[PDB]
Length: 258
Length: 271
Image 1 (cartoon, each protein chain N blue to C red):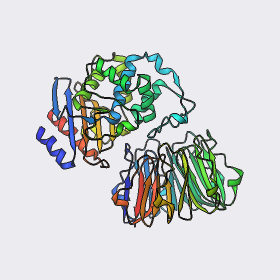
Image 2: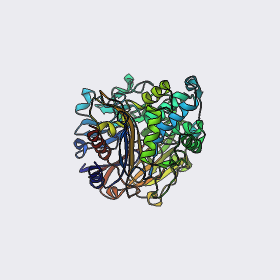
Image 3: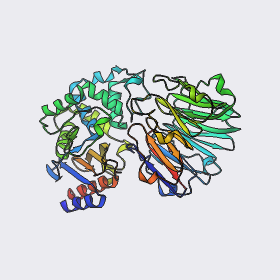
Image 4: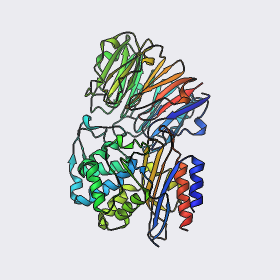
């Protein structure tokens, strides 16, 4: 219920946005669904989706080279393969699995920069998402700043299109969801809030002003998938987020869809 | 340590979420990319994502440990002069050479490399793609301190800095000032630090203000540490932080006894 979401905001001293879609019943759950939050690393799953839209699977095998000049921070994978390169597909995988920022930037470049990413989303009917900056400055999350923001409803709708809709053919959907499964960056968020026998493919987000997000497609054992977007932020630039907000918001969603 | 403070970075793997068991009575902390380690009463504790086995603690680390260090995928401990290593090993960073299995006085980890200081001699193993584990002849005697970076390593000999590995942003070009009187060194990904009689000296990349050392850290500093793209200094129990928009929160404005910088997460031990 909305009462539960509201209490969570107060419990954790945070602003919360939620949109969820049970694709089995087309039933939805919403909480501040059209309010803007910095999307932070959650764009990586969607941009990987755009990459898949615009490239053959064979194209993912191409080697991309880059140098120490190209590295930004939060890049554990790319900093390791600097100089000798990685495949395009390995790049997308790094962004999605390790939230690798340099990988995110290379992904951006491959689909035409933040504005190429925005354009592809516009083409899918998303007129809400604003993508303006590369990593790592897109995580700035200044209150009232529309740059690099979206809403739980817009993000969730995009994710549904990519992972359980017609934005990708089935084989490419499968590559995307595989990339999104089994990643540690997801452990304290949606995955922590749903039963252990559910399968969770997610992409996490963390930014300034205590921005803490998670989006996912999840499968209860005997059901069609549920698409979830949960975004959050705080008043102070240097605020510390609490993963439990996200996990508990997810339990609320599970219970509502029981 | 009365308490422990961890802050900064995305904390995407929980590397900055210190568990209760490591909240107090901690002697030291070591920060890796996906994990953290603490040394408490001779026992190695750890937290984070155990992606590579770096949190799978060898029985020997359960007591009598003297020091710890951590890289991207691996963990190191020093016990009775023997270097103990575990976790990811694709570059040979956990394959401890016999020479480092006794008599070792200090250890340090690079991102994919491990270092030991034995009777003044730096011993290095693991990745050598950027020359970081080829020890300069000069660093093979009279060394008193050392540290590993991402693509680099650093040592202090006769109070002068020795630096090797990648030099893309000039991070291993040692300034005149750091060639005598230096007590300690710390390497970032693209910058390096030295501590000279309480004055922090920084060189290399400054695109993210890494080498823009704050005035407060120009004297009276007792300790330094470096993450990838930020740095820390300890001064009369107060932590000074700079680079990549890092700040020191009010919790570390006093009563800090030691500092540790993981690649992204900073740690402060309080007395």
